[PDB]
Image (cartoon, rainbow, N blue to C red):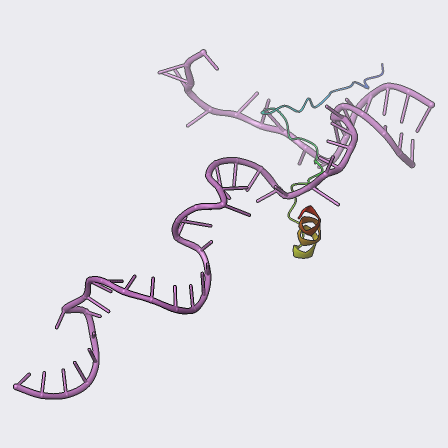
Length: 42
RNA sequence: AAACUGAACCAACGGGUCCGGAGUCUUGUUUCGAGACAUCUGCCAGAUGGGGAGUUU
């Protein structure tokens, strides 16, 4: 009687609370960080 | 897929404490629209201008 059972969250657009995602790209960085990147882009 | 008020968190689990579950990558913007334009910025130039100033009559 082993009741260990997988119960996957199955994240979908409307379904379950997702796991935390890495927001690094869309994050708001401090003023000097976005600035020392953009200066490279130029 | 006309609609007519339910619930969802703090991982279950799988693989060899890590990696999955939850694709990886970055010549780099937070994303979208416009864009070398103008309602952008500064100076120079004209027109208008009793809205306002001075004075005369």
